Image 1 (spheres, rainbow, N blue to C red):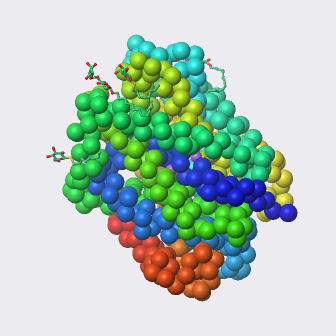
Image 2 (image 1 turned 30 degrees about the horizontal axis):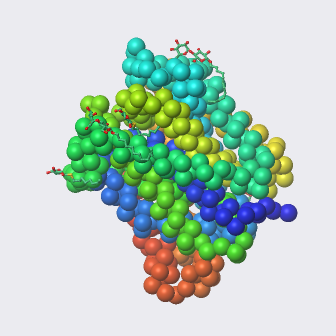
Image 3 (image 1 turned 120 degrees about the horizontal axis):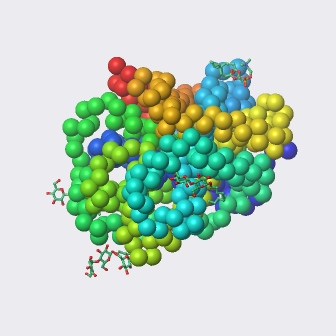
Length: 442
Ligand SMILES: CCCCCCCCCCCCO[C@@H]1O[C@H](CO)[C@@H](O[C@H]2O[C@H](CO)[C@@H](O)[C@H](O)[C@H]2O)[C@H](O)[C@H]1O
Ligand SMILES: CCCCCCCCCCCCO[C@@H]1O[C@H](CO)[C@@H](O[C@H]2O[C@H](CO)[C@@H](O)[C@H](O)[C@H]2O)[C@H](O)[C@H]1O
Ligand SMILES: CCCCCCCCS[C@@H]1O[C@H](CO)[C@@H](O)[C@H](O)[C@H]1O
Ligand SMILES: CCCCCCCCS[C@@H]1O[C@H](CO)[C@@H](O)[C@H](O)[C@H]1O
Ligand SMILES: N[C@@H](Cc1ccc(F)cc1)C(=O)O
Ligand code: NA
Ligand code: NA
């Protein structure tokens, strides 16, 4: 007896609650900042349109048709065929992403706690930068908040699809959006807008002569859409034929892009206002945003509201991360949902511990050459497993399915849009992924 979404809106809100999270505010800010701004942004937007939306609809189609996990969907639909390595890669991508995703989500909790206990109301004597560096370098303090966030994620995944994942507050996501628009409006009035908006929207094409910017653009695209690791195959496996998938794919990609763009209009005028470099790195928003909340009279409550709504977005994103291997181990080992969520959840928490330490005592340690542990596991997950698993997912429908079945299961016809969707799964998206892989790694 497999689970289904109880409500009709349950599927689209789950997929939206999974795509909109830390990647839109935290990750989109520091990757766009260190990749130059507008030229990376255009490549990113182009990848969202011509690669992201089709592969999202591909994941939806695969999951609903098979009614099975990330891996089981390929076993079921193509028995004995090697397409299930994408689900396998997707499962491993969940262990890795959620490991460090919970570290960054723990930072949200720590800042939330400091705004409840009235600590970060005024600037600390070491500044907002030094406050952040001292917290993340601390060996044990980030672990406490990381484990705290993981317990919240395990709890919801253990409760189930009907009573846990789907019972997410329908108001927190539109409230996060209203606050980002209000805050993007405020930072436009701080003095660095002309330089922040030019950085964000006036392209410097000299950046685009670097293979790494395309690789960072395709990774941020796959990351922010919860794409390439079967998470949308999993959420699609709980929906019935009473659903139109193409509108869901466009809506998730459209809304998810709206957050990142607005998050950019909020962050970068503030960065140039504070005279800060756009390449600050992973802790950019954690240094820039507390400064912004300090310049506001009612700023403490803004930070309280911001880190509540942001953590809620991270909470629902982590739930879809954990649900991917959990659905695997429920079928594969006949584990119960509570046993798999707790076991895998505790394990993934341990996996992220070296990522948390790599901001401090393990900062000198590297795995892949020139990247620390956090950046090494983020790289192989976001830059290797997510884009390759997406490429295989696209070739699966484009070349392993009959055209009529691909169109019928995705609620498309042989119209211009159906032909267009089949064209990008068959050629545009996988070849673009291929060219980005080839040009980046020599
Ligand atoms: C967000 C909602 C989550 C609900 C869970 C509620 C958890 C409540 C338990 C709080 C435990 C905090 O634990 C305690 O936090 C304070 C900060 O306030 C730390 O404070 C310490 O760390 C910082 C480093 O950033 C030092 O600069 C500071 O001088 C020092 O006092 C303590 O070393 C730690 O022992
Ligand atoms: C409440 C619903 C939320 C949804 C949308 C809300 C939008 C929020 C807009 C807040 C933007 C405030 O932006 C802030 O406004 C005042 C002017 O009003 C500016 O203040 C500036 O102009 C005013 C008057 O011209 C002077 O008092 C001040 O000396 C000067 O610094 C701030 O430099 C600017 O940072
Ligand atoms: C609200 C979204 C609109 C943001 C658009 C900003 C992108 C173009 S900025 C533009 O860059 C030029 C040189 O780069 C300067 O000559 C101009 O003074 C300046 O206007
Ligand atoms: C709680 C709602 C806050 C929404 C976020 C927008 C922040 C803008 S607040 C703004 O800060 C100024 C100081 O520059 C005050 O002088 C103004 O009176 C006040 O309007
Ligand atoms: N898409 C989420 C992160 C994510 C969730 C689920 C995934 F399967 C992958 C990635 C974000 O942008 O924060
Ligand atoms: Na996102
Ligand atoms: Na989310």
